[PDB]
Image: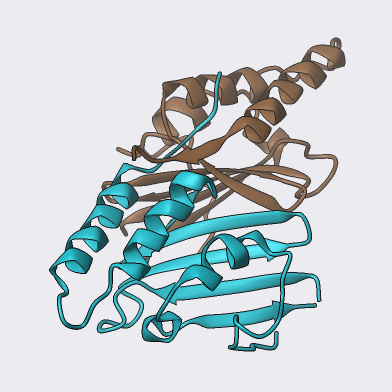
Chain colours: A brown, B cyan
């Protein structure tokens, strides 16, 4: 339940850390929330549109051996497979904010929305 | 908020109601938890293994034109696409029940487990 801040110093085995968070320029732009779980877990939240609060969020519940990843748009949360494709795309989004080229950011965020709207949870029958 | 019980009385436009819930012969055996939402929606929860409360359940959230379906195993909840495949598997599970011969039923429940472990939430990148 405690929401520390350190992530630039210490190290993790946690995939989402050593593959997205640490690889993002200026985390504080996206007003990150990071908490410690009991010590066996990490619960991460990043705003995708920091300007409009909780409009578009990325959430990652990490545990000892398991990770669960969720895109959330206007209050509707969808789970998505935690994999490279997602890590990358997430980096494309967050690493794309440049004041001298907002339109580029605009687009890649739209790219992620598309992914959001395109997610289906399927089984092999 | 409120929770009825006779899915045989009222008529519904809810698709989970007409494609599944009304076609279940011994609905009562599966300890249904059916609530109405602000009329506007239906919250449904069925026990796949009534013998072990909340071990394996199916949840369905219906609002006006939307439905979301979940399978929960040992407290782990996964969303699953509400499609014909889904509706056919569930009916096969709830209607295979026969107190005078349960092997068929025991096996189809396993078939639903297999489905659970198989679910993935993917987006096309």
- For the residue pair B98 and A61, the one nearer the viewer reads as B98
**How many numbered marks does the figure carry?**
0
Q: Is residue A83 above or below residue B86?
A: above
Residue B83: tell me if it is visible.
yes
Q: Quadrant of the C terminus of chain A?
A: top left
> How far from the left and from the top, in percent, is residue B35?
64, 81
On screen, residue A112 above or below B1 = above
Q: Is residue A22 above or below residue A69?
A: above
B33 on left or right of A48: left
- Seen from the viewer's position, the closer of residues A98 and B53 is B53
- Give residue A46's position: percent from left, percent from top: 63, 42
Q: Residue at x 64, y 59 (%)?
A: B15
In this rendering, position of residue B56 left or right of residue B65: left
Rendered image quadrant of residue A41: bottom left
Left or right, B63 with reference to B72: right
- x and y percent of residue A116 in the render? 65, 34
Q: Residue at x 38, y 54 (%)?
A: B89
User: Is residue A1 in view from this perspective?
Assistant: no
Residue at left 18%, top 64%? B104
Q: Quadrant of residue A112?
A: top right
Which residue is painted at 70% across and 17% down in the image? Answer: A96
Indicate whether A50 appears above or below B27: above
Location of residue B91 in the rendering, given as x and y in whole percent from the top left corner? 41, 62
């Amino acid at each position: 339940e405690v929401n520390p801040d350190i992530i630039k110093d210490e190290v993790f085995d946690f995939v989402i850390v050593n593959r997205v968070l640490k690889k993002i320029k200026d985390l504080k732009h996206y007003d990150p929330m990071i908490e410690k779980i009991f010590e066996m877990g990490l619960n991460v939240e990043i705003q995708i549109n920091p300007e409009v609060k909780d409009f578009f969020t990325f959430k990652s519940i990490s545990t000892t051996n398991k990770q669960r990843c969720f895109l959330s748009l206007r209050g509707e949360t969808r789970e998505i497979l935690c994999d490279n494709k997602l890590y990358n795309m997430l980096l494309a989004v967050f690493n794309s904010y440049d004041p001298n080229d907002l339109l580029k950011h605009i687009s890649t965020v739209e790219s992620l929305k598309k992914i959001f709207y395109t997610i289906t949870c399927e089984a092999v029958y």
